[PDB]
Image (cartoon, helix red, strand yellow):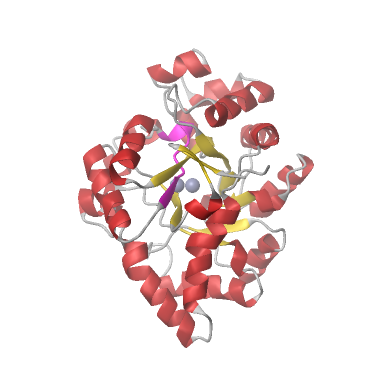
Amino acid sequence: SFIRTFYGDIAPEQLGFTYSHEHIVCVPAYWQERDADDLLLDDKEKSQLDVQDFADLGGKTIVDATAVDYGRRVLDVAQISKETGIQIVGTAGFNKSFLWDGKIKPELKPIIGDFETYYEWIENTTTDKLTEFVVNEVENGLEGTPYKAGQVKFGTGYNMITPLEEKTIRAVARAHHETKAPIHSHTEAGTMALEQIEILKQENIPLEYLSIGHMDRNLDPYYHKQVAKTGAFMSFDGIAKIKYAPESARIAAILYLVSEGFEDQILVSGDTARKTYYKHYGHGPGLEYIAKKWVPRFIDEANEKGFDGEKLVKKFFVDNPARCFTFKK
Ligand SMILES: [Zn+2]
Ligand SMILES: [Zn+2]
């Protein structure tokens, strides 16, 4: 088996230290149209400086969760990978339905069809044709480029799975059946994981093939244990996001799952989606933050609370991503 990166399929042992959910260069139509400039990562050289910080700290791989509705700049990301040496796992599929109001860029029309918005495209395209689109991103390349995606994604809304969202879940599940690519989901504020899981079960998807994004947004031990029992990977990707929770709260939730025997299912990242989050755009914590500052604190705090901090860090950033992001064949 293998992990599919922009520059080739690699052995799991080659993945190394990994951030499991990030954004690098992207210009989401929905946000661009609303002049939300902070959500546009629109400078390749600035993004590259953060990725280089990661590389300098011993980082090896970034999973780039930018989906088709989030304004990919695949060629820029590929160039960054080439220049920094950081391996990139790209993402096929969809991010979240509120983005679908955004206009379809000219480059997508030859691939997707002559549709004004993502909503129009998704509403008027059969599930099977949506599956074809996702499969082609994994097998042929993203957005007319030769850089293939290494995971397939879908997303749901705040305490909602709409009919169209459900359609995309089924399209992505079926794309998994064809390609065997790992599956990632967006949960809005950490909601709807159990309902996502029910749809995937109807589609005959083994749940250990799924990583669920944004579990750190809903810090509920009972809910987390319900999700973990299915075998799904659980992504804590809001590290440093004090506006959502203090770091202690995220760390406590992680350690609860460890105490209940689920350490092998935990993934960690920063979901760095803003200029103000990048060191070299707006002087935020940057891609350096987790490796440089969070890791030593987690190790220390976990050790203080009786855990094996170093072993856990190795699992969260090395062993677990190597298990999660391998194709299922
Ligand atoms: Zn997301
Ligand atoms: Zn994201």
Q: Nearer the viewer, residue 6 or 190?
A: 6
Q: How many marks?
A: 0
Question: Magenta segment range?
Answer: 61-70
Identify whether 72 is placed above or below 123.
below
Q: Quadrant of the C terminus?
A: top right
Q: Residue at x 47, y 75 (%)?
A: 310
What residue is shown at x 66% (from left), y 49% (from top)?
209
Please tell me whether residue 279 is drawn above or below residue 156 in the rendered image.
Answer: below
Whether residue 44 is visible: yes
- Does 67 appear in magenta? yes
Residue at figure coordinates x 46%, y 32% from the top left: 69
In the picture, measured across the screen, residue 168 lies left or right of residue 312, that is right
The quarter of the displayed image where residue 256 is located: bottom right
Residue 31 in picture, x, y percent from top left: 36, 36
**What is the quadrant of residue 181 in the picture?**
top right
Q: Residue 104: x and y, percent?
A: 43, 22
Judge by depth and name the residue closer to the eye, 27 or 117: 27
Q: What residue do we see at 58% from left, 43% from top?
A: 156
Q: Is residue 217 visible?
A: no
Where in the figure is residue 320, as x and y percent of width and height?
56, 60
